[PDB]
Amino acid sequence: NLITHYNLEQAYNKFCGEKLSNFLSLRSLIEKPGTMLAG
Amino acid sequence: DRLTQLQDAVNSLADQFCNAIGVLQQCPTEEYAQLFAALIARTAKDIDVLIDSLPSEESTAALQAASLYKLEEE
Amino acid sequence: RLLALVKWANNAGKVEKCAMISSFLDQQAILFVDTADRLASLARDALVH
Amino acid sequence: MAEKFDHLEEHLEKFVENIRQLGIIVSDFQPSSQAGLNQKLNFIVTGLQDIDKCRQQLHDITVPLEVFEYIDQGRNPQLYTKECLERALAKNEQVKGKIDTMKKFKSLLIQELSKVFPEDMAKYRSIRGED
Figure 1 (cartoon, each protein chain N blue to C red):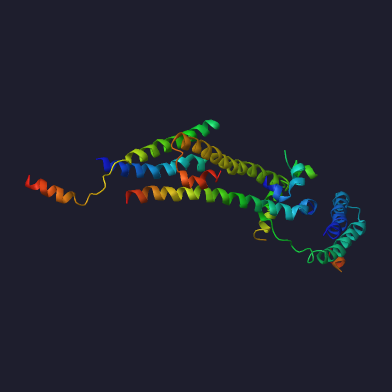
Figure 2: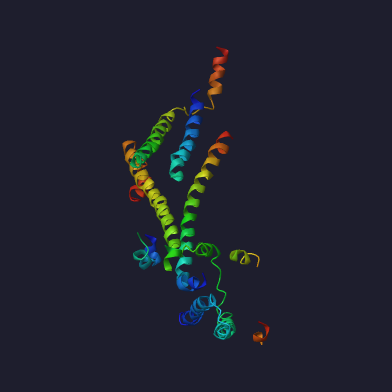
């Protein structure tokens, strides 16, 4: 229930009973990573 | 004898107090609940024993020496 | 991947509060089973002494 | 906030879309329109600075590292709430099932207790009156 005492119920509707591809390496960096004159 | 049982009854008392939860903490779904109706029912039959185990000791047992003593002479 | 951060990062306070809620729960069950083993300790150790 | 979020959007959003531009032309090099291309680069520099301005106040916001992985697996958050939601099921199962374990446990308990001596009598004051 206790979402009852935890207010998530909107997210119940939304979120009672794709994603990446849905809404339309690098991670290792994320672990251990006159200019006109130049080119 | 009959003592050792009361000891056995106390052993059951805990034993019960444990596995009578055992599955419960670890998880046929009301069947469960009859596993449990049992679980107690076993506890029951135990408490029964407790009850009957019970009526067993006789209560002025110190003097029974001096009784023995008159008997000794016997 | 970023703008996705941007485009679904709306969810923080909830989703944390969620994971929190999870953890709140899980600890009840811990408490639960833990209380049980607690018994079982008693069962053996207690009895056999 | 949102409209700084939404700024990070339409601006930095515009920055992604501009990139759409960047590639789409840079398939094909016309000897000069690198003027147009590198004016987009110019866009890239005015961006990158302005961005970082939009980026050191972006807060590097605290890291949902894993759910990161989850959207680092592109699997969008909502499923998180969803999946812990499925746990929350399992857990509501456990918890209230246990209450049941009780409600029978007691129930059938007291049942036999009555089917056994229901004779914790005086202290059944508390007991009964405890039901």
